[PDB]
Length: 538
Ligand code: SRM
Ligand code: SF4
Ligand SMILES: [Cl-]
Ligand SMILES: [Cl-]
Ligand SMILES: [K+]
Image 1: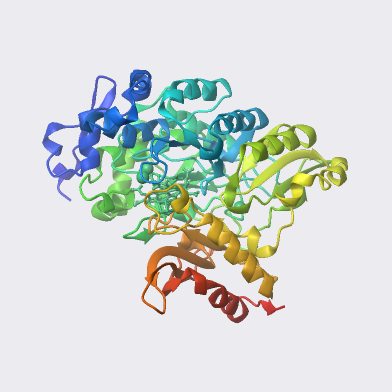
Image 2: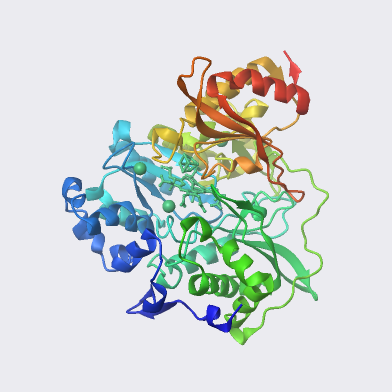
């Protein structure tokens, strides 16, 4: 690689970071959008206040404003549902480590409640909240209300650092390696500039996923993150080995690889900044399918990329990885659903199944009430789109198990439901080829009616090749497609994936059978479970 390739391609101008004029040739249309107007100005210069006053019909009449609502607003966590819910916006938070409070939960419920049939909420595969139904004129007031309850929505979509994922059992697990909350909190604060906005990291060539590992279970899926912090001692000090470049896309899926770098715990933020600066400065900004960080790592090689991170460190040093990390390879991933003792004697947590991650305002209020009455007002989200309520005195569990809402959000659903993960799908998402959430529940119910099993089989349903519900990690994965019935009629279908493994012995699954009509999946899945996962016909 020529030394010229290493010239930073962006420059700080008037508080924002912009592509230098010599590096603007051949860019994709998303880069053109960012050049035409800095997305962070919608928040940091209160551009949203004026935008929110313009009728959508008018907004749509010029490129600048249309790009504001369709692209730039994703820097404020607002996602126009142009195709499937025109003029309404999904809103996505920063929720490091999946931790929420009852007050935050009631606040979000109050927002969606206003929108009636256009409103609901969802837990995401990055243990995050999304709310739905938002109209533009309400945005200024929602931004205020979020701030008031201690939340931010900043930089949660498009070319930004996505939700910092941690251990759902952080601080409460007798077997934890290190509490991930301080680190995921610190990263989120760094990314969002303490909720004011951080333009130093908001003009990336592409999205970028971080996680901090604290569990032997690897609940955090470090193998599929752009940056994963693996806890490891080095020379008697606590810190993290660094894995880089994990990603999924329609074109390519790749597991994270070692940077061959270790940092002390206190250097979590400095090294996040260094990697992000390297990516921002040097990343390719052409074909959007070749813009994720791994593509830069392949072009420079890992050592060339590592050198780029090193020079952006303070003291310009980056220690080599420690030979062993703290994660035990001998580990059976633990079920967190149900009632489990905390490390704090006299206390339990409860994992509740949230069917396909979907909740209404009334459900949110009920979960908030349980957290206040039984817990400490805390609710934790998981990447399987479930919840954990921690800090329940164990003597209250008997009363808790009789709560009527636990029949809907169960601490002990059937085993196939425990592992079921499903993306938004075509109810709201404009990229979706099929309906996912309702369909996956129905198929799973019908499959479980036919077979009993003891293995915790994990089934993931995703509505298009963007694979937001990560079908490549599943025991059985279903990727939406259109296909044909026996009469050649168009029907919704799934490509069926097998071979995904999670935890330390991770592996990416691959298509096993293409184009299965969704109405034919039950018998296929019944047979797969009997033949490959030890299921027994009822
Ligand atoms: C909500 C969520 C799925 C879910 O039901 O849980 C989701 C939903 C969306 N994804 Fe995603 N992604 C979700 C996690 C993922 C992950 C999983 C993960 O992070 O571990 C992936 C694959 C992993 C990865 O990115 O490396 C992911 C891969 C994508 C892709 C393809 C990325 C690429 O390199 O090509 C896109 C399209 C894009 O970015 O260009 C996409 C685009 C989108 C959009 C914003 C598309 C569009 O605007 O409609 C979806 C919004 C639909 C909606 O209304 O909810 N989303 N998306 C997840 C929100 C996570 C969060 O809180 O931040
Ligand atoms: S996988 Fe496709 S359908 Fe599902 S939320 Fe992501 S972009 Fe939408
Ligand atoms: Cl996006
Ligand atoms: Cl759309
Ligand atoms: K779930």
